[PDB]
Image (spheres, helix red, strand yellow):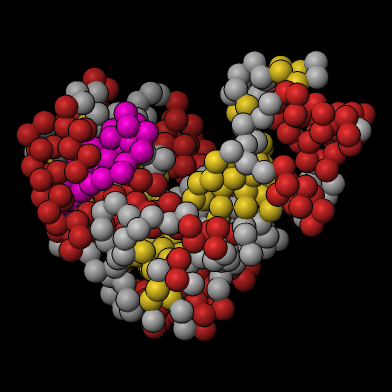
Amino acid sequence: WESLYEKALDKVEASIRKVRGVLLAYNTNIDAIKYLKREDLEKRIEKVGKEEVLRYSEELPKEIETIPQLLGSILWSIKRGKAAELLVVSREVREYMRKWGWDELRMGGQVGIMANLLGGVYGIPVIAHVPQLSELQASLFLDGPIYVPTRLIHPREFEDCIHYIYEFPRNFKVLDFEAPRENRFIGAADDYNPILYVREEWIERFEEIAKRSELAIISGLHPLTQENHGKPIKLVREHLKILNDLGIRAHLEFAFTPDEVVRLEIVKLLKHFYSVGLNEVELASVVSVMGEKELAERIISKDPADPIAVIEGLLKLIKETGVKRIHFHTYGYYLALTREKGEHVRDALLFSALAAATKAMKGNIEKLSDIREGLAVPIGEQGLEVEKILEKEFSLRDGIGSIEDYQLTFIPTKGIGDTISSSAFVSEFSLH
């Protein structure tokens, strides 16, 4: 496998920028990170009222309308050491948070994060959808062929949708509480992304914008609820159809969607996507909502994820959607089921696994050339064991086989899931 890993990287290294442009849509925001300090926190709590704050540290509010609710929610996460996120619907509270400030800024949303990766690192032209492109928002994009449609211009040439993170380490102490695990609470001063807001220009002239791309990656659907999914899903469906009529392949990393009704709806929406990516948790979630409760559990029961179970789950997915490309990724191995055939599918998976391994050690991919670092990372033991399993069930030749007109491709691993499926999707078609 090591030789195939080297050859794959070498090819993608030279071919990835062949992609003429990638359309990235919907969710983009600003992440404002604050490393909490006990003195500062306790002082602010006393100012607003210790008793008030405490009540919310016991029962998380539905939303954050007042300062006590904000601080209490922070405490809620601390005393339990568990993540939680709530919308800040009060101007007053947003102003409070703005003044409170932050220690570091980071690009948020899959659109912004992939623009920086695909455009800022891989050198591929990116057309991004940014709900609110403020000066601060724009400053978070890296240099490179990163654009937004009105002619295409760089973000820097164009309100703040800020998510305040409030992070604390394990055993962080405040009042008489102690964090049982390193975590964070997020105050989202953003009422655009939660509803999958779409810029007016993208609603009115999507075809013209779409024509500047070769591939598309859609994200931001997971937070939609049964109450607000109506209009956005209809819009996304309209865009997908247009993309499909143009020959533009669209991809989606099926991020966990809490609302079960929306989850099922996005599953069916896949009939209009060319490609979908997901891990064991997301696959189990999807299979479960399709009624296959038995499979769902069996897909996440064993570790590594039971390969036979995963494939059966994947086959159920294709049966209901006809999705032409599926990229399954977990710790230990990746699997792809594609109507398109060839070793290029394997080249792409291998390249994406190297990207993941690189971001795993380095913690951040800054140059394409840095991916070569993943070459020296030994192949996982679990990876070889799963291969043994799949060679018993299928006639795999160097990780390649087939099933029901779909090519099956396996790869032993050494990437936020997004870095993985996006890198493989884009690299695969750069070779086409």
Which quadrant of the rendered structure holds the N terminus?
top left
- Most frequent secondary structure within the magenta stretch: helix
- Give the image location of residue 279, x and y in percent: 40, 40
Is residue 131 positioned above or below 309 on the image?
A: below
Which quadrant of the rendered structure holds the C terminus?
bottom left
Q: Quadrant of residue 60?
A: top right
- Left/right of residue 387 with respect to residue 83 in the rendered view: left
Is 164 colored magenta in this rendering?
no
Q: Determine the residue positioned at 10% across, 45% down.
A: 10
Is residue 135 positioned above or below 238 on the image?
A: above
Is 359 colored magenta in this rendering?
yes
Q: Determine the residue positioned at 64% across, 64% down.
A: 159
Give the magenta part as a residue range.
Answer: 339-368
- Left/right of residue 85 with respect to residue 375 in the rendered view: right
- In front: 366, or 264? 366
- In front: 202, or 330? 202
Can residue 24 be seen? yes
Can residue 270 be seen? no
Is residue 322 positioned above or below 361 on the image?
A: below
Q: Determine the residue positioned at 27% across, 40% down.
A: 355
- Give the image location of residue 377, x and y in percent: 21, 26
- In front: 376, or 430? 376
The count of marks equals 0
